[PDB]
C-alpha cells in the first residue's frame, strides 16, 4: 500500500526527465518518446500535491563517542547557498 | 568622626545603581554561556 501510493504520487510525468547523451540524434529520441512515454501520467490525483518547505538549518552538534575505533571522523558545515544564486559559484 | 560620610554615601548610591544595572547582565551572560550544557541530552548506543 505504501509503495503503491508512493509510485502513484511521486513518479509522475511532468517532473521526470529522459536524458540521453552520446551517439544519438534528437528527432529519433523525441519520436521514440512520443511513441512510448506518451500515455504515462500527468493526471495527478486529488490531494497532497508535493511542494517543498524551506527547511530550518538548526546548527548544533552530535557526537558518537565510540572509543573502539582507530581514526576519528569530524564534519562541520554552515549555511546553505542554494542553486540559482551565483553565491554557489 | 567621619569626614567622608557624605561622599561615601554618594559612592554607595552610585555603587547600588551600578550593581543593580550590571549584575543582572553578567548573570544573563553566565546563563547564556552555560546554556549549552544545561540543554545537552544523552543517548546510549551499544550494538
Image (spheres, grey):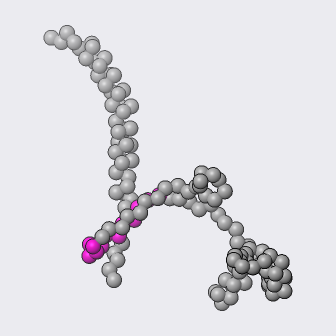
Q: Quadrant of residue A65?
A: bottom left
Quadrant for the N terminus of chain A, please: bottom right
At horizontal 34% and vertical 75% (from top left) the residue drawn is B44
Front residue of B41/A7: it is A7
* Dominant secondary structure of the residues highlighted in magenta in the image: loop
At horizontal 35% and vertical 28% (from top left) the residue drawn is B18
Q: Is residue A64 shown in magenta?
A: yes
> In the rendered image, is residue A18 in sight?
yes
- In the rendering, at what x and y percent does residue A12 appear? 74, 79
> In the rendered image, is residue A46 in sight?
no
At horizontal 19% and vertical 9% (from top left) the residue drawn is B3
Front residue of A44/B6: it is A44
Front residue of A31/B32: it is A31
Q: Is residue A29 shown in magenta?
A: no
Residue at the limit of the structure toward the front, as seen here: A23
At horizontal 37% and vertical 43% (from top left) the residue drawn is B29
- In the rendering, at what x and y percent does residue B46 appear? 32, 80
Residue at the limit of the structure toward the bottom, as seen here: A1
Residue at the limit of the structure toward the left, as seen here: B1
* Residue B46 shown left or right of residue A35 in the figure: left
- In the rendering, at what x and y percent does residue A33 appear? 80, 82
Q: Quadrant of residue A61?
A: bottom left
- In the rendering, at what x and y percent does residue B5 appear? 23, 14
Q: Against A64, is A55 above or below?
A: above
* Residue A81 shown left or right of residue B39 in the figure: right
> What range of the chain is rendered magenta?
A59-70
Amino acid at each position: 500500500a505504501d509503495l503503491t501510493e508512493y509510485l502513484s504520487r511521486h513518479y509522475k510525468a511532468p517532473r521526470m526527465v529522459l536524458a540521453a547523451a552520446g551517439g544519438l540524434e534528437h528527432r529519433q529520441l523525441l519520436d521514440l518518446a512520443q511513441k512510448h512515454f506518451s500515455g504515462l501520467s500527468g493526471t495527478y490525483d486529488e490531494d497532497a500535491v508535493p511542494t517543498l518547505t524551506p527547511c530550518r538549518f538548526t546548527g548544533s552538534e552530535i557526537r558518537h563517542r565510540e572509543d573502539g575505533l582507530p581514526l576519528a571522523h569530524v564534519a562541520i558545515a554552515v549555511e546553505g547557498p542554494g542553486w540559482a544564486n551565483p553565491d554557489n559559484v | 568622626a567621619e569626614p567622608e560620610h557624605d561622599h561615601r554615601k554618594r559612592m554607595g548610591l552610585k555603587m547600588l545603581l551600578m550593581m543593580g544595572l550590571l549584575l543582572p547582565l553578567v548573570y544573563a551572560m553566565k546563563r547564556h554561556k552555560w546554556s549549552v550544557l544545561k540543554s545537552r541530552k544523552l543517548a546510549y548506543r551499544p550494538p
